[PDB]
Length: 155
Image (cartoon, one colour):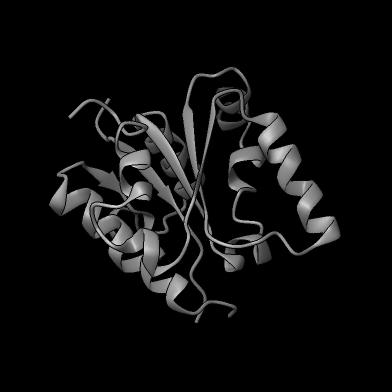
């Protein structure tokens, strides 16, 4: 309906080098300036109110994609939980009703860790897995950036 992507990352005030800058700075800037998509970024676009759970829910419904940025802080704080604790959000993931682009920025070191993630992948009906290879992919006009833009909606 009203957004081309909901953007799900984790920020803490911490296991992240240059990765943090890609997932907090360059990624939303490049998609929303240099390609002009419209993103819903929770730390711009949503006050924590008493209705936060249903606010966040009713914004995912209005988003054409779900981007999930697997910074190691995300695997730390299991950033995906919101999307499995909320009932409607869950079924949307398993029913195909929402397309999930999952930007993988690190190697899943973590025997437990590696397995939870596969049940995430399991539980999403429509999944794209795009791999971020450092500054190398961050360099605009890259192989990562093209891989990402038609996984985004039409123009």
